Length: 183
Ligand SMILES: [Zn+2]
Figure 1 (cartoon, rainbow, N blue to C red):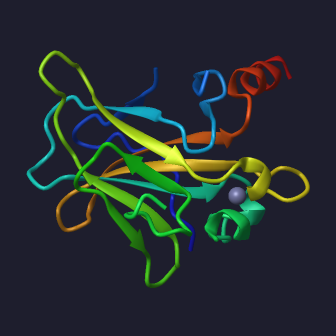
Figure 2 (cartoon, protein in one colour):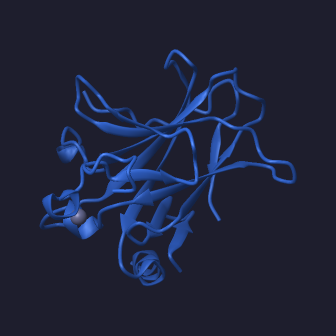
């Protein structure tokens, strides 16, 4: 095998930040968002990564007992913006250089964009992700949670940094965040 979820700040001090259609809980390190809606994820670095640095997002199941299962869209939702393959859970909006990738070995999907430094007047780089299936399509009986793993990689695909966060795609993110935080 499964992709590692191990936090790895690496040489460049790679960290994530987060800002309802999308709400994040630091307490739970969990994003709550609606299907297909904008999910802004911030990339923070302490120094600039090398030229050709790329940013990959992939979903895995959080529970060890389900980690070998590939996270994909349910049969209903699978059966597109013109760019994303229909099976891919995670899309990127507002980027002209998106790559949708299927691992030849593990069959796992991922979505990659070039690393861009922050825009003038900003301190971080923001990527807008969209999740294209609900957690209720995704986790059968006991509602199986997923993680998004964000990796900073060099141009050859070598690991430069890694962070992750749990995600719940749901109709009412504010309500679910509240409930899970109370629990
Ligand atoms: Zn679905």
